[PDB]
Image (cartoon, rainbow, N blue to C red; front, side):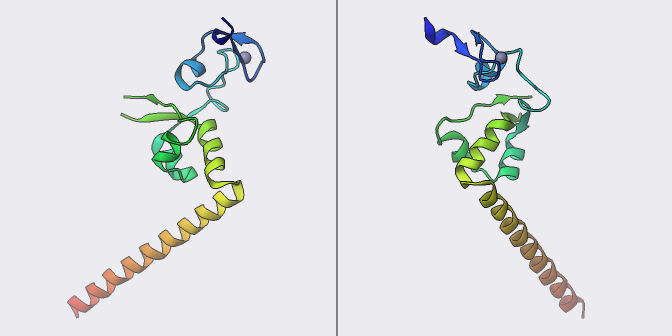
Length: 126
Ligand SMILES: [Zn+2]
């Protein structure tokens, strides 16, 4: 059965089982797995914050990204997160523009809120 033999996307050789295929449907054999760099895992919260991904970006866009549960955090392949982010945002440039818009909005809002509380303080103490 040809279906049962997976061509490795790294070495090009067929395999039947691997960590990456079992857990993530990533067709990469155990020989080619690079846990420290290419096939490193990241937390859901980290993936979401760093690459600006909504849950539906992970779960509803095709293919849905798979995760392993650690003990209770969901871990995703960074590689897949990054690919999904480029898909959703269109380009690295558009993602970088969004991250900059987000950081500037967040700073502006924190500053405004803090300053209003300082005013409220000075006003109440006065
Ligand atoms: Zn391989």
